Length: 185
Ligand SMILES: N[C@@H](Cc1ccc(O)cc1)C(=O)O
Ligand SMILES: [Cl-]
Ligand SMILES: [Cl-]
Ligand SMILES: [Cl-]
Ligand SMILES: [Cl-]
Image (cartoon, rainbow, N blue to C red; front, top):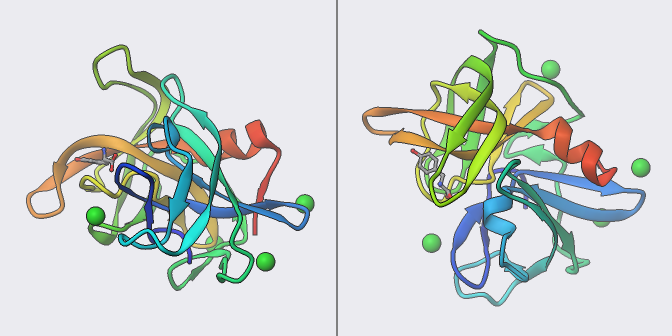
């Protein structure tokens, strides 16, 4: 399993963001709105291949969370599909970026603003977000935003779709890495 692949909680489907670790303890990052209220995560819709257990969630304000792997045999590739990931970096305005998710696959675009605020309603306001003209659809949440070998963001939300076009906001991944003291590999 790698960044962008489907992940299933007790209630629905999101996307794996990045595989990360502290030492030989492996985890993955995803969206906080996906980890909120979740316990176990599975790799398949039939919920027979366990991945692991929710181990942190920050949503709203931020939108990141972390899952501790309990499945010792599944491959945990330090990649986003075929893209090798080696480090994390921060977005800049105008930067070419790529998202991968489990609903719509791989889509590219550009960063249009930094430090964006998104009000999802119901008190769920998030701050500090990377705004882009990349599209996304439900189920893509949590998936990676990257540029080359650099991990940049986690899919939070937005408007539109991949057929007609859209606007998507991403949580900076560096914040999540620092909050938990974990690293991409
Ligand atoms: N909110 C979706 C992600 C999303 C992104 C952009 C959109 O236009 C719509 C949905 C997730 O929880 O799975
Ligand atoms: Cl599904
Ligand atoms: Cl380490
Ligand atoms: Cl391993
Ligand atoms: Cl690179």
